Length: 18
Image (cartoon, rainbow, N blue to C red; front, side, top):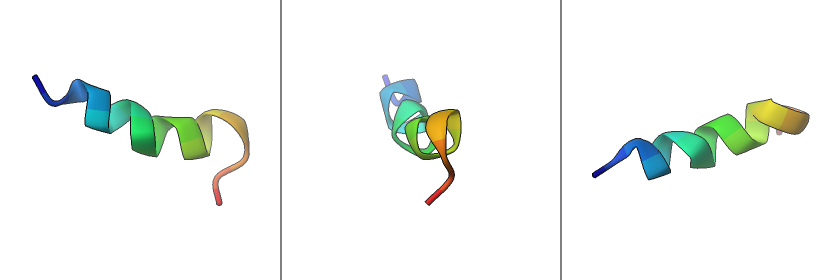
């Protein structure tokens, strides 16, 4: 597992970016 991490960074971008 690790993609869950990716979502962390993808969550930032997902919505805003910062």
